Image (cartoon, rainbow over all chains, first blue to last red; front, side, top):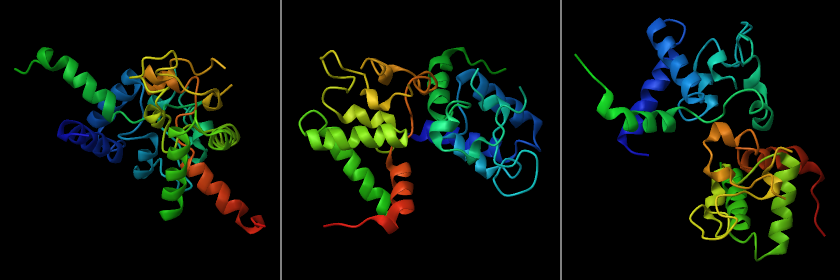
Amino acid sequence: WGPLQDSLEHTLRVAIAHYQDDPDLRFLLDQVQLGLRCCGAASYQDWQQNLYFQCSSPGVQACSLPASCCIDNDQCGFGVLRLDADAAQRVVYLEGCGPPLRRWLRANLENLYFQ
Amino acid sequence: GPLQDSLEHTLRVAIAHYQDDPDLRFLLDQVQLGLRCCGAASYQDWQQNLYFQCSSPGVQACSLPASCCIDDQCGFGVLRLDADAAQRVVYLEGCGPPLRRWLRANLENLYFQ
């Protein structure tokens, strides 16, 4: 609940909002969600803030999650935002990437090289 | 809002008194089983229970009661898992939200005598 995790969750929310218009953030966010087995910043419901996945339009992805949120193909997250959490967790990861990304950064601090 | 906050207060009281109050234990088991949920806000609320908390020295440390399970020993050791692993065995979301929805849906048939 400190500033490091708060900062990481800010970045994750920016990536969620810009998932369709910034390929760099899309790739990074997919790598985090796939690799750390998590969805969103605090929770999978953070994806309601992305206009394509938000439950608010007739678009194909409305009320859905991207496939990098799915447990263990491309439509695996379809409609999951409409579900009760007990149903959703059979299909996608519920907890956000904030906590595991904080743990990852702390573990990898000494091998993060910048040049 | 205040309704859900009140329900989560009650759920946390039941968690704390799970072993010493059979009425709260039964009620909490029935809510967790029936609404498919674990805890008040989340399954990690069980860390506030003296027997299931991971810091306890007893055999049940870092475990959950069976009423939290998706499918008793089904909850043994689940509080130590990462959430992605835990959600394979127990419900992650607390009973606050579904109990709030249940009460709102059934309000009109709630009478008392």
